[PDB]
Image (cartoon, rainbow, N blue to C red; front, side, top):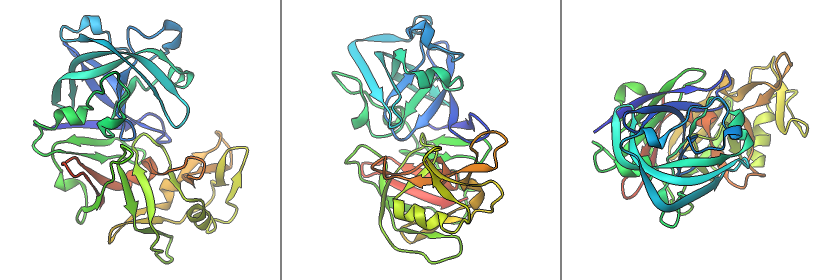
Length: 330
């Protein structure tokens, strides 16, 4: 079995990507944030307190002939940004881009945090981390990917995120027409339940590649690229009039500027993020300041290769019993 679904940025800034998901019978189509940095499938629902739903489309279990209440199971999750939600749990049919899974644990939100209520475009999250992170209790539930694994042509999914443009989540196969060169595979640690890997270093612009280990997670639901302070200071040093701003909370630079590329290594391979990717956009509309697309991980406590990194790459999540991460230039 395979699936293939278009994923689209929710705004002109590429803050996040949404992908339509089909839940229930007959099918209820919601727009979910595919999040390789968590492992809960959660949605706005019939059950969600009314004054907390805000333009979002909801999943009504009672209109699905194939939904079933998972007796005594509840969940509660929070994200690095401080947002949260909680509720109880249905099993149901879930289809992504052709690929269907029966008895997928569909977590129904009874309450959502104010952040979610303001985000009109996001109808919930589909988590693609390891199942060890699932919040359901007393027994943890499998992700979409875990459940699909047996029927997939290959235990893998690939993320092809676009730079101000839709792209592609693929399940069960690697599309050779989508990248250039060859995929470079690197080892994953599952010890924290993340897609966690060790980058072999970095270069800024046209200068020298420093081999230094960067431990980091590949996280499709994190907008920016967060790296050790001293790496980040190295980058923005090449942008004159770049400075760190307390007020706006990170490095800011003149929209005027041509930003240098950033290169990060994967084994012996090099992936290069074009300067234009790191120009996130103006801090307010009309401003001559833009917010920087690479920022310090120091306050997060883990390095995150989020959307700014990943969209420069064709990325293969390899879900074999020993999982690997593949990067290719595209």
